[PDB]
Length: 156
Image (cartoon, rainbow, N blue to C red; front, side, top):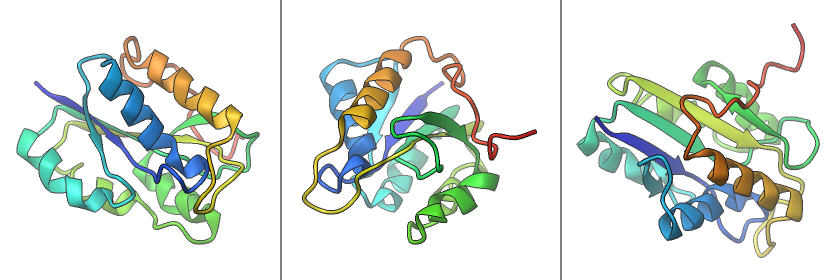
């Protein structure tokens, strides 16, 4: 029926602007019929907007500290977002937002990107720009997870 893309981040808080740069690119040139939405570093406001659409699926995108190399990309899941977002020692455990939507949306998905620079009045660094570009290009053939690896403490 409907499939939404919830960008999250702040465009001048460093690499944190991951969602905002993706949202700009998708707004300029759509992909995969995603109903792009930009939470604008206050994504809880947009839960109501998402709920009006009762989406079949949702994908959410922001930077996430993963202890990886800058600009590395991973799929994440609400069971693990709860720890991995506060790996920053301060970010809200964004699974709280997913829990307001996963109860009615058919699938809720997250993609994180390893930052290197975070703080107000900083641009995004080149490797995270390249990561956001890679996600943006994937979105027209992403299918379900874009073939991106799933963050799992990189062990088995």
